[PDB]
Amino acid sequence: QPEPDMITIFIGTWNMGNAPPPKKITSWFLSKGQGKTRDDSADYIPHDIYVIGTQEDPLSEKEWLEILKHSLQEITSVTFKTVAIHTLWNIRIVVLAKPEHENRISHICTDNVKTGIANTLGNKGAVGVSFMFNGTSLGFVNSHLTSGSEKKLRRNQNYMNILRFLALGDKKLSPFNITHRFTHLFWFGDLNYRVDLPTWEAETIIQKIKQQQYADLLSHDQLLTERREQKVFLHFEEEEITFAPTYRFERLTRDKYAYTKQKATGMKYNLPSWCDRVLWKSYPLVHVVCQSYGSTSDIMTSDHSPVFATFEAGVTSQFVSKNGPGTVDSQGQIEFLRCYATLKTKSQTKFYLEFHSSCLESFVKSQEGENEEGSEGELVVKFGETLPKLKPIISDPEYLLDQHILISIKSSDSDESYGEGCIALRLEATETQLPIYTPLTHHGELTGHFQGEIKLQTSQ
Ligand SMILES: c1ccc(CN[C@@H]2CCNC2)cc1
Ligand SMILES: c1ccc(CN[C@H]2CCNC2)cc1
């Protein structure tokens, strides 16, 4: 049986509004309704992995697993295996996979983060799952962020606390947060960002939704505007939105948005908004293609509509050679030339690099760089040709060109990372000096850049 080089992944997010679901929810898993929908000719074709995030979920794990598995069996005639399930309060993630993938999936990891302090600790946060699919690491985060149109900054803070504190993926990647630990990271949920228009415009917004004039409303979506200002979700991608706002509906119809302030809303307006979102971040030069992104029209138990997204995701095989794993392959090497980091820090310490990759037997520390002042105030840390030569475990270019090197720049004084990035080895040429580049982040915020040249030797 050949190992796959692509899988398809279903992501769902649904804030259930503390109500049980209706008897049929298959339109969700079939990507049918509004937006970018899946072709009818694919309806019997199972996705490889289904990741279901709920918020305000009233069901037990058992109750929801029975609904999910029976739903997928009806659609596909496949009995899916449960990879993982994790619940924090009423926030839940379920991962299901086709039975043929059971012996491809390993290193399963679950975690949660509770957001807020005192008043604001008690029901928001995130759950996540990670695992390996053969040679590819996959991460999934379902977050329910702070509600309310005037709390976008709180949502951004919630996001930072989640990516700092969620402990998924390889713990040996100690300098790296979840935004660097996975070949593919999917982050979805009731992110709760709103269409920021005046309350008086509520009926105008509804008009525009009825006319399917979404681009105009999207120019005021707080998640797009905060992302464009680099306040949140830096270096993530979202498909274009072509479906109506998924919140806030009257229950048992989709004909009516319930936006007016009520005691039950804390006297807050809920103008129609795209609360419910799917974003992703994949390592450079890996295949990832969004093939659906939309909302259902026929599931009406909640004041939110479910959202679906589906993806093609490149995956790699487990690789065994006569040499690595268990030793190095002397026919392989990775050389960094003429490298320098540009940092935004005002601190004066020396810095060194750490190189992490599953193509190395263990992480590699460089010598300290040479600090200089940039012509616009910046710290520049020069490594020249001083960086260690990296010795991969496997030299076969069918393996090595698919790998990635994570880089941390660390203070000699504290050994704390000031910035993290990622370099793909999917080069235009081997045995050739080629430019490389990554932005550097810390806690998901831009802290600098790393650039230089690489020279990759493979066995070919
Ligand atoms: C929100 C809106 C627009 C953007 C910029 N576009 C991407 C830059 C790299 N590729 C496209 C980021 C966030
Ligand atoms: C669903 C998918 C994967 C798994 C774990 N499989 C690993 C242990 C045995 N071989 C690999 C359990 C449930």
Image: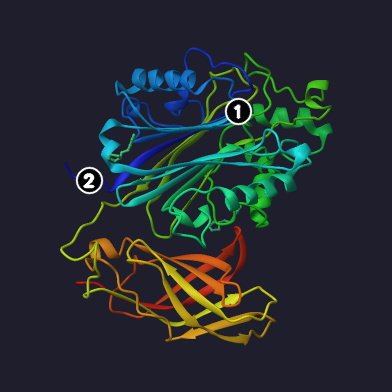
- In this rendering, position of residue 137 left or right of residue 299: left
Residue 382 percent location from the top left of the image: 53, 84
Q: Nearer the viewer, residue 101 or 268?
A: 101
Q: Residue at x 75, y 36 (%)?
A: 148
Q: Is mark 2 on a helix, strand or loop?
A: loop
Locate the C terminus and report the quarter of the image it occupies.
Answer: bottom left
- Is residue 6 visible in the rendered structure shown here? yes
Q: Which of marks 2 and 1 is nearer the N terminus?
A: 2
Between circles 2 and 1, the one closer to the viewer is: 1
Label annotation for residue 423:
none
The residues bearing labels 2 and 1 have C-alpha atoms spaced at a distance of 37 Å
Locate the N terminus and report the quarter of the image it occupies.
Answer: top left
Whether residue 257 is situated above or below residue 140 in the rendered picture: above
Query: Could you classify mark 1 by the number of other residues whose Cα lies within 10 Å: few (under 14), some (14-19), or many (20 or more)?
Result: many
- Is residue 277 visible in the rendered structure shown here? no
Q: Could you say which quadrant of the image residue 125 lies in?
A: top right
Q: Which of 35 and 224 is in front in this view?
A: 224
* Residue on which the image places disc 1: 90
Q: What residue type is labelled 1?
A: Asn
Label annotation for residue 3:
2
Whether residue 22 is situated above or below residue 367 in the rendered picture: above
- In this rendering, position of residue 339 left or right of residue 412: left
Answer yes or no: disc 1 within 8 Å of ligand 2: no
Q: Nearer the viewer, residue 239 or 101?
A: 101
Q: What colour scheme was applied to this rendering of the protein?
A: rainbow
Q: Could you say which quadrant of the image residue 428 lies in?
A: bottom left
Whether residue 425 is situated above or below residue 433 in the rendered picture: above
Residue 181 percent location from the top left of the image: 46, 55
